[PDB]
Image 1 (cartoon, helix red, strand yellow):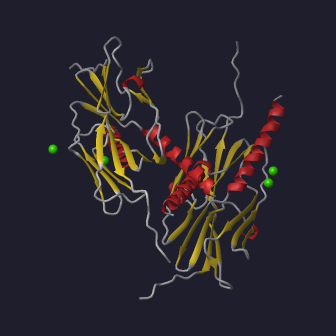
Image 2 (cartoon, rainbow over the protein chains, first blue to last red):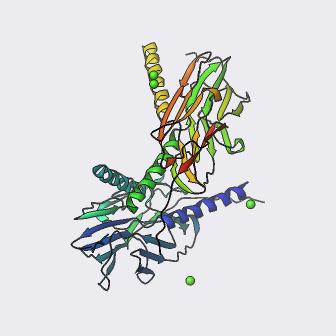
Image 3 (tube, protein in one colour):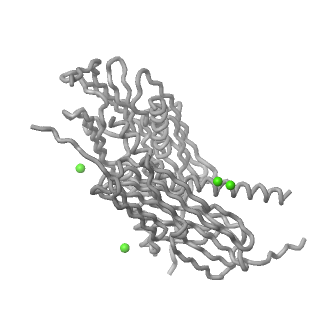
Length: 123
Length: 123
Length: 122
Length: 123
Ligand SMILES: [Ca+2]
Ligand SMILES: [Ca+2]
Ligand SMILES: [Ca+2]
Ligand SMILES: [Ca+2]
């Protein structure tokens, strides 16, 4: 039945959007100059609608939201409305140090200041 | 094992990037006013390095290329370097009409004029 | 060690994926003008296995399963879902209903085949 | 040279069977309630021809053998004839404790008691 066929298309497309919502965004992590920088491909979002935060845990969290409204017949709606990404941080980040987030060309770049030395424990 | 672990980690990172290369970009497709619109999330790319193609078989093809060079330690390399996506268009493209592609905020917007007909039963 | 922990989890999944691609091994032979396909497909629900014949003459076996365990897991190799496409050496008989039987982790499929090929005359 | 092609095919079939023998069977290992459990997919084997052994070195060994012969033309013979798999257990096996092996639906399940301890900090 066509009605049956149509429903499947809707479900697949919705599954697709969700899959992207979990996967996006891919990130690159590297440490440079005592600086930890995270780069994320995050196309089509407002700067206001993006939030970057650090938990006390050294976890790095990225949240973004958008509304997409299209007028016309719709064949696919893959793009993710809602983004939540939680990122493990390899090393402890200096407390009370400036953190820079810049949003360019759909790319979110985060620089975290890096502390070189680790106090180690005896016994 | 230490060397092996590093090689393996490097291998694992390569796979993750490859997975992204396969799934990016997500696209939205909708048609209004005899126009088909494709919207794709393609962050962190250069317009000069992006190619958009229309095919005789009615596919739309998007190719993206970029160079990633990183200085210092690398913890993650998820972000895609090479993009190849082939989309089978729902509607036949108009044979002789202008086709437009734009790149803003990491988003590639493609507009294609469309050829179509629907038949009305005569009573 | 957490990342080392991270590496291990991925390797295990990669392993699971590898099994999903390879499983199952196939034995193919022709008996009595029938094509018999035997696949080793352990621990799957019979209700959960689908066998179908392609227009192109490919033979397809589909199976999926859920595996859930309680406690620490050291390995999860076993395949959750298998999609296998088999190209068929001989043209399949039209009509000619085909039967599938599943026992002891083994799925056996019997297919009738046309015994002759007509030849075009130029 | 079609017959030589056939010999080559027979060799290739032979290799495939060999590769499978190396990779079969895939195993699931989990430890719960002092029992370590191994689940392996070993379809189409006689119970009598399957051997399960526990090693001094703490390995678990699975051995199986089968006879496969067919009548008429053979197009493929992937399925393994003889199986040897050595698994090194994550945790110590409890000495002289009952171990159970069950084979059903082509699945071999092995239950092994383990010796382990954890230390609780005092005060
Ligand atoms: Ca319905
Ligand atoms: Ca609103
Ligand atoms: Ca051999
Ligand atoms: Ca051998």
